[PDB]
Each structure stands twice: as C-alpha cells, then as structure tokens.
Length: 266
Image (cartoon, rainbow, N blue to C red):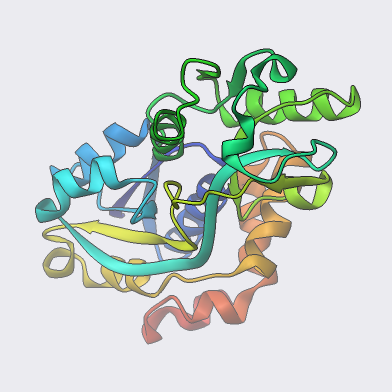
C-alpha cells in the first residue's frame, strides 16, 4: 500500500485531527502511519522529510521558537483551523482580570503555575510571559502534561482553590468549567491565531494525492470541540472515534480529498 506519515504531539485537538486524517488516508488506500513525538522532534522530522506532514503547527506565536529556525525546510500550506488563543487562565471565582495583577499574589497560588509538556510552544511562551511581566521569581512554572494540568484544574475548582494554568482555545475546558483568560496588555501570548498544516519539501512532487489532502484539510469548532470532548470522556478511543467522525461527517470529509476518491466516503 502507498505510504503517508503524519507527526503530531498528543494534545487533545491535535490527536483528534491527526486520527481523523489517518482514517481519511486509510479510506484512500494508504498505510497511514501517525507518530506521537515532542514538538521539537515533530518540527525536526518535518524538516528532514522523515514525516510527510503535520496538522499541528500553532503560529505565529506559540511555535515561533521552532518555526523560525526551520521554515526554509518545510512548506506552510496555510491554516487548517482559525481562531486559536493561548494565555493565562484562572477559575472565574479568582478576582483578578490581568496578568499584571498576579504580582504580589503568589501565596494564593502556592507560588506555582501548573503548565503542560516541557518544550510545547505554549509552555515556552508562558515562561517568556512570566519573565516579561516580572513574575518569574514569584511563580514557578511547572512542566507536566495537558492531562495533569487539566486534572489539577478540575481538582482546584472542586476545592474552590486558586490555580493558574496556561490554557487555550479551542478546548472543552471553557464549557465544562467556569474559567477565564487573564488580560495580556502587551500581547506576549499573541492575538487570535491559527493552526497550520506543514508538509515536507518534496511532497507535492512525490505524492500529489497526499499533498492535496494536507492542502484541503480544514475544520471548525462545531466539529473539533465535540470530538475533543468525546475523546476526553472515552480515553483510549481516539482512533475508533475518528472512524465514527469520518462516517458522520461525509460531506465535509469529501471536500478534503481529490475528486477521484470522493465516492469512497459515501
């Protein structure tokens, strides 16, 4: 069978998207392999062509550190999703509105910001924001993972305790919990951005059908949020739930594939 390789990092939305594309390529007759790696390795592998594509690039702000360094070694096809935001998040019952109001209040947070995976773009920029706003001596930024960060948020809110986390949209946490972004006066965390699809240098030449799918993949909150939420409630079922997603959203999926293949999704 023909081959395509997709790199991703195991955050909820990117794992949802990557498993959906895996299912799409399988239905087109590919041995579609997906590879769960670190952000750094995903970008490295893309640049050396050891994967064919990623649908996980958060730009320009979150992934600046990786993207700027390697942009001559991949092709940026545009956005597959528009409307991202990353930033500092607290439960709504915490009575501050801005990142600067955190100054002097470290004690209420046990002097910690409960973060995600070391090296994630959002984690990098969060550390840069803590430095910029003069908070880094008072708040220790803790690396862990999306799962640990969300379990800690869930725990703190049930206790009615203050907690500070880096969070982002799109995420079901904003509908499941009453939480808020803090204001970011100098926009260190970026404005509203997008997730892009990047492919290796030779892909357009080598496998135009695979290029076409990467080039046409696009979706929105009404598809990704229910899927991210369902996957969270059904741990370990992301591939099965992607199979169901592709069956349930035939017409949209059709738009991502060359004419030749569209009836395979009927």
